[PDB]
Amino acid sequence: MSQSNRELVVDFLSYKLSQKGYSWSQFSMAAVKQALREAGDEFELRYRRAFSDLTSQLHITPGTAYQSFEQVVNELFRDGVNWGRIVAFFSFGGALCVESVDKEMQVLVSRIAAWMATYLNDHLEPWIQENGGWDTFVELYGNN
Amino acid sequence: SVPSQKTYQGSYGFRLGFLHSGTAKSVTCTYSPALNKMFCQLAKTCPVQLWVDSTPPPGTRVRAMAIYKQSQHMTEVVRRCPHHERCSDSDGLAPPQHLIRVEGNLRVEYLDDRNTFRHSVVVPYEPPEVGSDCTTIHYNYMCNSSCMGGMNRRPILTIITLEDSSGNLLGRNSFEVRVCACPGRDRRTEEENLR
Image (cartoon, rainbow over all chains, first blue to last red; front, side, top):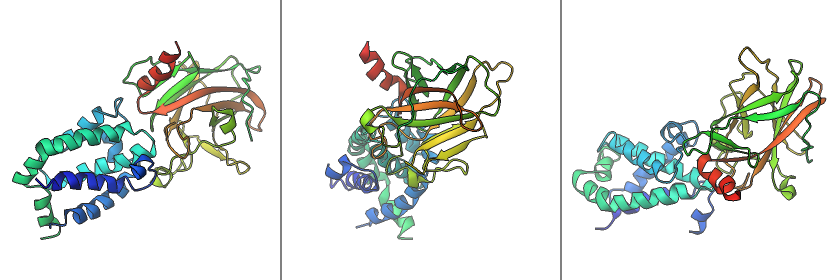
């Protein structure tokens, strides 16, 4: 268990958290990192327009700490093991995390990341490292 | 430049009216009459009513300028956070620099002061139609009170004033605002904590 999946998820998150408007986030191979970096960054610029998919997905839920987690997580399960949906999934969290620190909410990303990282190694990691996730994504993205 | 935050009722009786949505968790916006503080959500519509004792001449100017609650911070202007201005959330009528915008009423203008960079919204007085006792205007807050850089986790005071077509003060009121993601939650942190 190299935790390549768990590492990439938090790595990409930290990468977007280093965009603009970060306080606490500043003081505290298959080339999956590159693949997620390129596609994720290009998607982020479209999500950071405020009036994007994020607005319709989150819609400012009256419980942006736990309800937001289910909302984002359920989105992935709304399609399933889809390499096209996983991109949007990362985009949602990626753009959301930036605005979470930019608006000094903290609890938003601090809680979601915690639950996400937990379920990640708990079920997502052994799932990806069996059925196929980022490994198969690169196959059609940068190895096709 | 510190605007006159005096409760000018005037002859027209410019009173502020708000919808009492309650202390429910699931709410887009709610007003607390216990502290004259309105709680709003990010990018959500906030309905404000103008309880005018005397109907003002149609065509008047409703000016809304937000300042900070802290007297020592009143010299500052309420702006957006680092990652919000470059978001390009402009529809074409509303600028990306303005935090307060107007919805519903197409007749919306933005007054940008070049003396102290005072961002303020100004809309023409809409005539109350049948069934509409109080002029209800839709105000949209495109930022949270916790937004670093701009509000920087500081409560704001939105001054709602009514001037004539020229600029004569007919009425002026003010209320405290707290924009977040859960009005019902934050309300229990202040109102339910002061009683």
